[PDB]
Image (cartoon, helix red, strand yellow):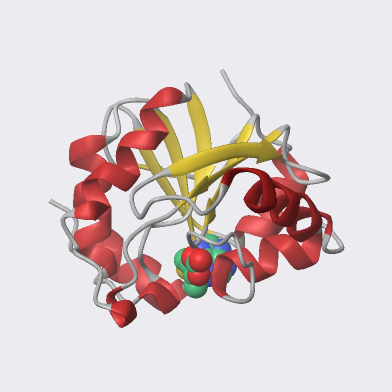
Length: 167
Ligand SMILES: Cc1oc(=O)oc1CSc1ncnc2[nH]cnc12
């Protein structure tokens, strides 16, 4: 038993809800919240901008030191950093950005990072401003992640479409 509430169960291990991931993190304080990161951990907009704003820019400060020490992530890769006031940990995962021409097959590799964590609160990777088809992202999530994932979909219209079209 865990504290996630109001989710629709899609599969044995995947759950979905129309929610703001920032507000969901602040209420659940999950062990892991996933950020829709880029390789530079520049948290400007989308999910990343919103999570970082909710940390009063502490996520960005921590991220800049991480990059200064380690260099950029790989597309499809991840790193674990602090969850600040939102979660114990933040798993920063880089899905391919279609608006940069990145290979969409890297979406499966990106979701594989979720399997290193028993339970996660997450957005759909490569959705929103990363330009991928969210229906496809949900399919890859279901077919790749084996651990327990709670997906927050900000937009109510998209949430309903994701549920209604789910196979
Ligand atoms: C736009 C975007 O940018 C990013 O990096 O990921 C996403 C995923 S959609 C999203 N955008 C904002 N708040 C949310 N809460 C739950 N899903 C979302």
